């Protein structure tokens, strides 16, 4: 389960962690995060995120 980064501000989504405050529980892979979700720091959509190929 891979991490994703917001390319506009650097936030990193960690599927272990999730984004619970926004309704994205731990263990939610990026692709299953509802498509209306936006970066918690900067507010941008998911289409500015990239998978962290480390
Ligand atoms: Fe961001």
Image (spheres, rainbow, N blue to C red):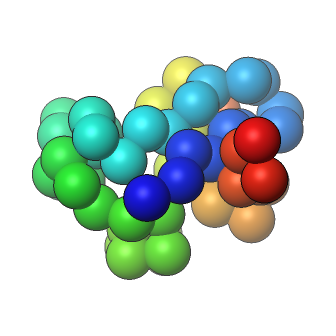
Q: Residue at 62% x, 26% y: name it.
A: 11
**The C terminus is located in which quarter?**
top right
Q: Position of residue 13 (x, y in %)?
A: 50, 39
Image quadrant where residue 6 sits: top right
Q: Residue at 36% x, 47% y: name it.
A: 15
Quadrant of the displayed image that contains ligand 1: top right
Residue 50 lies, with reference to residue 42, above or below; the image says: below
Image quadrant where residue 19 sits: top left
Q: Nearer the viewer, residue 19 or 40?
A: 19
Q: Is residue 26 visible?
A: yes
Q: Nearer the viewer, residue 17 or 54?
A: 54
Q: Residue furthest front?
A: 54
Q: Residue at 28% x, 40% y: name it.
A: 16
**The N terminus is located in which quarter?**
bottom left
Image quadrant where residue 29 sits: bottom left
Locate residue 24 relative to residue 42 in the image: left or right: left
Q: Position of residue 45 (x, y in %)?
A: 64, 57
Q: Is residue 44 visible?
A: no
Locate residue 1 relative to residue 54 in the image: left or right: left
Q: Residue at 53% x, 53% y: name it.
A: 2
């Amino acid at each position: 389960m891979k991490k994703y980064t917001c390319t506009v501000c650097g936030y990193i989504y960690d599927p272990e962690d999730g984004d619970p405050d926004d309704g994205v529980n731990p263990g939610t892979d990026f692709k299953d995060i509802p498509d209306d979700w936006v970066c918690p720091l900067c507010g941008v959509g998911k289409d500015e995120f990239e998978e962290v190929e480390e």
